[PDB]
Length: 8
Length: 117
Image 1 (cartoon, each protein chain N blue to C red):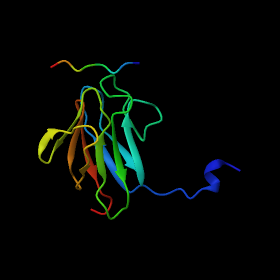
Image 2 (image 1 turned 180 degrees about the vertical axis):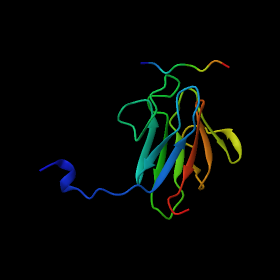
Image 3 (image 1 turned 90 degrees about the horizontal axis):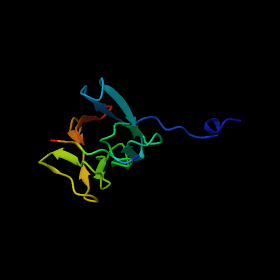
């Protein structure tokens, strides 16, 4: 799977 | 006849501690001589299967038990952060790890340990 972005 | 019974299985030379957080409880990972890949993939030496960790996130290379491990980021999505001095580690740029040094992979905080302390 594609790496998830962390939301800040 | 097992593959591992033929080999010289080298003991761990260090430990990476992961602190408790949104991803789960604390955990220790043995580190070995050579390339310790940190990443989401199941085959990684330090396998952190959290969606924010890159498939191949970072690498801790241990050339000798009397030389500082070499940390580098593999162009991870969410980065690798060091604190000596604090900054995001650019891909390729090596960082030598001291005993007790703290690092972040994405939002996971870790601490490196020698075994002779």
